Structure formats: C-alpha cells, structure tokens
Image (cartoon, coloured by chain):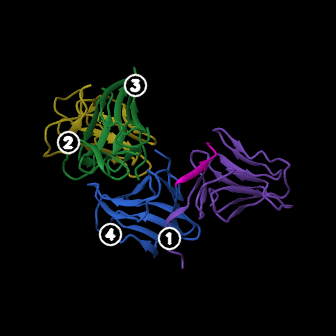
Chain colours: A yellow, B green, C blue, D purple
C-alpha cells in the first residue's frame, strides 16, 4: 500500500508514498520531498547522489542511499535512541509522514 | 476526529457494526456480533479472531494512546484487550499486505 | 461506522479532540481538555458544559444505545455521564436551532423500513 | 435545519427535508415522497388533498393534513404504542427518515 513504508522496504528512484493530495517523493535529483496543501518538508539533498533510493531502517530512521556510494547520503533523524525493531512510516490524512514504532502487538504471521 | 483510512486505524479511532480495514483480499472486521475478525477471501476464511462473538450487540473496537486495542460494549465494559501497552503517545494499527494486523508506536518523529 | 453529520450524533458515534456539532452560531465541542462545551457566538458564551476540563488528554464522547452520553478517558474510565437510560435501541443527539442539545430515542419507525 | 423535523413543527406544501442526495417532500399533489438512491417511500396520497402539509405529532407519527381538513389525510405508522412526548424525524446519511423519541436528555433553555 502506497500510504505505508515498513522497515526494510525501499522507495525507488522517482517512486513515492501518496495519500489523497499528498505525496512523499524520492526524486531523481536525490531530494526527498513532501508535497502537500500545507507545509512541505525536504531532505534538502539535491544533487547529492545518483539513482537514489529511500529506506526505513530498524530504528525508525529514513536512509537515502546512492548508487555511487556505500554509506547513506542522509539519515533522519541523524541520531535516535530507539529499540531495534520493526517501524512504519505512514502518510496520513493529515498530509504528513509520521514514523511509528516499534511494533508492540500483532496477529500471527501471516 | 481523524478521517477514516482504508488500511490503517489511528489512536482514538473506533470501529463498529461491520466496519473494516482492508488490503488486497484481507479484511479486519469489527462484526455486529462483537467479534473482531481478520479474514482472507474469505474462503469465508478466518486467520485471527478476538473470539468474542456474543459478548455484545453494540460493541466497538478502539485503539488507545498506549497502543492498546480494546473491544468494548455499550456499557463501556471491556470484552477483549491486547496484552500490550507502551509509552503514552500516538499509535497506529495497520492491516498489512502480508496478512498481519500490527500495532506500531509511539510516534518517533514526523514531517509536521 | 456511520458517516459524520454536522448537527446530529447517532448512537455508537464518538467525538474527540475538538470535534463538534454545529448549527447557526451554536456549537457543541468535545474539547482537547476533556470538557464538553456548548457555546453560542463562535466560541464565547458558554451555554452548558460538563465541567470536566483537565480530566484527561485523550477524552472522547460517545452516545450510547440507551441514550446515555459518556465522556470517557483513554483508560476507558467514564469522566462524566448523563442520567439517561432508556430502552435498548438507536438514539440521536441533535443540536437544535433553539440552542439546546437533545437526545431522542429509541427509534420508533423508519422509511427503510 | 433541513434534515430534522421536530414534534409540533410543520413541512409546508412543496417544501422538504433534505440531506445530501435525499429529499422527503410534501408535494403539491398531496403525495409525501422520499426521493433517494436506496429504495423510496411514499404515502401514496396523490390527489387526496389540497394545500397539504406534514406534521410530526407527540406520539412519533407523521400526519398529513389537508386544507379542507378536518381529519388527517394520512397517519403513519397507522397505530402506535409510544408515549406522549417530544419526537424527532431525521433524514439521515442512510437516505432514510427515522423517527426517534421521546426526549431523554436536554441541555438548558436559552435563555
């Protein structure tokens, strides 16, 4: 589903989360931007990489990765004190992306 | 009141009278019989249930601000609750593409 | 789930976090401070209140299937309840043009039928 | 508000309740018709009256009254075991009109 990104999943170059009028786009210029009828958000990462992709890690941080480099272009938040686990980014009805976790209850797989 | 979303339930949100979350061929339904059921197909096909059928005529399910999922009757008595609770905050219940319903929280960070 | 209506709340529906009923210059607001307030003139003159401010940060109001109105906290404890309790069925809370919020029920008949 | 009819109020000739795509109309032909997308309803009182009007009584019944009354043209439901009191008809999101009552709680009069 296009409104959700779970830990270990990736948003590829020029792909996006969307809900209604809002989109969170991993751009070809390597900038990650939230477009909404409101206050947007940017990684401000224009031109910092090639064929960039976005992943949500096991600490609730977004990582932008570049084809041309081993270490991430950007990680946000840069530092966290979270439990290692499964996290979810949701682009809500609020037109924002909120990261939630770790997982605390679930039905049995699967 | 938070607007209803097809595949996700947010803290403070409520479901009742056969309302559901859905993705693909999966449904998470708060049935009119007080039973919360995750079904696929349904080859009339239940994956998980609260097992609370017959405990109420006007039950609702609610996700709380401690990640708790409660099924509650008209009298406000709880007929099922998930074991967990976390830090006070905002949580989400997601019906996943893998057929699991999962609660995640609290909010680590947001673009807002 | 029943769709939200501006002037009426149906049994099983809930209001939270500043959600309201409205008609004319009247509103009934379930405030983010756990107080249920009925006011006249975009916000100001308070006609009625539950007086439950500060009782919770995640409170909700719910109209029940005996006509009762409960203000409930995150822990599911009831902060305030109205004194009503009619026969089991479906009820309606209407914010009327005369400035009163009134609960009516149960349902007698329907075109539905 | 056009989605509510209270006891003792009236819908006049060629006026209606409305909510979204639903209308409950007291027609000039004296027929009371629910127009919707979900299965209609009508009094079937075409031509039974003139300058007809619709009232909700203190038992939760609708009454159609005619200019030459004296007795109502139509009463619905036909017989009722309800208490005397104040009732409300709501044309809901279901596109139907449901009658609720009697009143069980109220905030204070203004004022």
Picture quadrant of residue B17: top left
Where is residue A8 drawn, in percent x and y? Answer: 23, 30
Q: Nearer the viewer, mark 3 or mark 1?
A: 3
Label 2 to label 3: alpha-carbon separation: 27 Å
The residue drawn where x is 15% and y is 46% is A80
Quadrant hosting residue B45 = top left
In the rendered view, does A29 fall on the left or right side of A57? Answer: right
In the rendered structure, are the residues bearing label 3 and label 1 in contact, judged by CB atoms less than 8 Å apart? Answer: no
Q: In which quarter of the image is the C terminus of chain C?
A: top right
- In the image, residue C32 above or below residue C12: below
Q: Disc 4: which chain?
A: C
Stretch of the chain drawn in magenta = C106-113
From the image, state whether disc 2 or disc 4 is nearer to you.
2
Residue A84 lies in the magenta-colored region = no
Is D5 placed left or right of C21 in the picture? right
Q: Can residue C112 be seen in this view?
A: yes
Q: Distance between the residues labelled 1 and 2?
A: 43 Å
Could you say which disc has been placed on residue B25 in the image?
3
Residue B54 percent across, percent down from the top left = 36, 38
Specify the farthest residue to the bottom. D111
Label 2 lies in what chain? B
Q: Position of residue A18 (x, y in %)?
A: 40, 37
From the image, tell me which residue sits under label 1.
C42
Disc 2 marks which residue?
B83
Residue A27 in view, yes or no: no
Cα–Cα gap, marks 4 and 3: 44 Å
Q: Which of marks 1 and 4 is in front?
A: 4
């Amino acid at each position: 589903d296009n409104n959700v990104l779970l830990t270990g999943d990736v948003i590829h170059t020029d792909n996006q989360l969307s809900y209604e009028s809002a989109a969170f786009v991993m751009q070809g210029d390597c900038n990650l931007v939230l477009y909404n009828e409101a206050g947007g958000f940017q990684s401000n990462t224009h031109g910092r990489g090639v064929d960039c992709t976005l992943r949500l890690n096991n600490r609730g941080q977004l990582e932008i990765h570049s084809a041309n480099s081993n270490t991430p272009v950007w990680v946000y938040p840069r530092s966290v004190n979270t439990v290692r686990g499964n996290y979810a980014a949701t682009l809500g009805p609020d037109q924002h992306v909120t990261i939630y976790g770790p997982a605390i209850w679930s039905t049995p797989a699967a | 009141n938070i607007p209803r979303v097809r595949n996700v339930l947010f803290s403070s949100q409520v479901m009742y009278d056969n309302a559901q979350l859905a993705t693909r061929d999966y449904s998470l339904v708060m049935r009119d019989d007080c039973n919360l059921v995750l079904t696929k197909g349904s080859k009339t096909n239940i994956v998980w249930e609260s097992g609370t059928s017959g405990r109420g005529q006007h039950c609702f399910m609610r996700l709380g601000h401690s990640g708790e999922l409660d099924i509650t009757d008209d009298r406000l008595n709880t007929v099922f609750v998930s074991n967990t609770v976390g830090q006070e905050g905002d949580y989400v219940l997601i019906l996943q593409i893998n057929g699991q319903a999962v609660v995640y929280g609290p909010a680590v960070w947001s673009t807002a």
